[PDB]
């Protein structure tokens, strides 16, 4: 049993971070980073060409 | 997003499959240029000895 502010704190912390730490958010972010790495590779390979 | 990733991946696959081709093309161009440079020497020796 806690205070109301502490319970809202813990509930908001979990319900926001677990939304942020979901593996679906992580896989979307790494696919966006993969797109970034891929057109960076496009630029570098075209520069070498 | 995966479609975009694989299209860029096959783009770079064809880029490598033309990269080795470009290595071959630089090779044959360099050989033909050195061939012409070696063709210069008959012209020089025929200009000198004759």
Image (spheres, coloured by chain):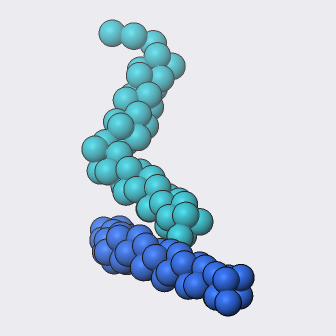
Chain colours: A cyan, B blue
> Residue pushed farthest top?
A1
Q: Where on the picture, by quarter, is residue B11?
A: bottom left
Question: Which residue appears at 59% of the width and 66% of the height?
Answer: A47
> Residue pushed farthest right?
B48
Query: How many labels, in total?
Result: 0
- Does residue A46 show up? yes
Measured as percent of width and height from the top left, residue A48 is found at 55, 64
Left or right: A5 in relation to B14? right
Decide which of A44, A35 is in the foreground and name it.
A44
Measured as percent of width and height from the top left, residue B31 is found at 46, 76
- Does residue B29 show up? no
Decide which of B37, B50 is in the foreground and name it.
B50
Measured as percent of width and height from the top left, residue B23 is found at 41, 70
**Residue A2 versus residue A25 in the image, above or below:** above
Question: Which residue appears at 50% of the width and 64% of the height?
Answer: A45
> Residue pushed farthest front?
B50
Q: Give the quadrant of the N terminus of chain A.
A: top left
Measured as percent of width and height from the top left, residue B5 is found at 35, 68
**Residue B47 versus residue A35 in the image, above or below:** below
Question: Which residue appears at 42% of the width and 79% of the height?
Answer: B28
Question: Which residue appears at 39% of the width and 10% of the height?
Answer: A2
């Amino acid at each position: 049993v806690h205070s109301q502010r502490t319970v809202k704190k813990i509930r908001g912390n979990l319900l926001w971070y677990g939304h942020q730490d979901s593996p679906q958010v992580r896989r979307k972010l790494e696919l966006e980073a993969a797109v970034t790495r891929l057109r960076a590779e496009i630029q570098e390979l075209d520069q070498s060409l | 997003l995966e479609d975009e990733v694989q299209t860029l991946l096959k783009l770079k696959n064809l880029k490598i499959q033309r990269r080795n081709k470009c290595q071959l093309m630089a090779s044959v161009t360099s050989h033909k240029s050195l061939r012409l440079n070696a063709k210069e020497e008959e012209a020089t020796k025929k200009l000198k000895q004759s």
